[PDB]
Amino acid sequence: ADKELKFLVVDDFSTMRRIVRNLLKELGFNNVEEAEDGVDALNKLQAGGYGFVISDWNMPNMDGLELLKTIRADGAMSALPVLMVTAEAKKENVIAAAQAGASGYVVKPFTAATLEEKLNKIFEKLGM
Image 1: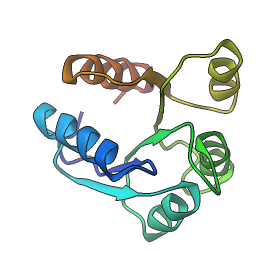
Image 2: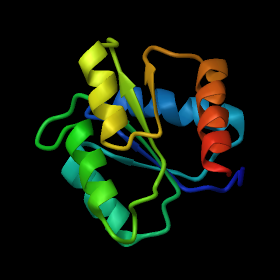
Image 3: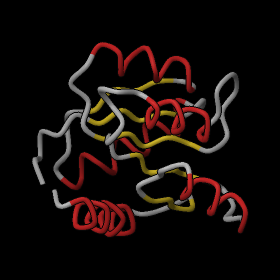
Image 4: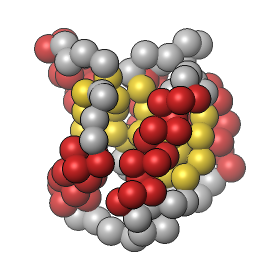
């Protein structure tokens, strides 16, 4: 996949955004921007040019599921890859995220190798 693919990392904790950004860096993905919640994320995506979204499931104002649903309901962005991040895997959460269009989901904390495996699986499924 394109190493300059523009990523948007969404979470309400700057430290966790920093962790994800650093893990992406280690994998060769340096074109990264951040957002603090679902609404802030939607504004950034409005600007354009994004190619991948990594967002937490739990955020205030608009959570991961609502952000995903809006991205999927958007005309220009409906196919945008979205990797959901969560602290605890829950059966219903996984199905809800999948049925809402999530490209994948991963449980944190995670390593570079785990993030790389998730990205590659999504890239392969999507044909990227």
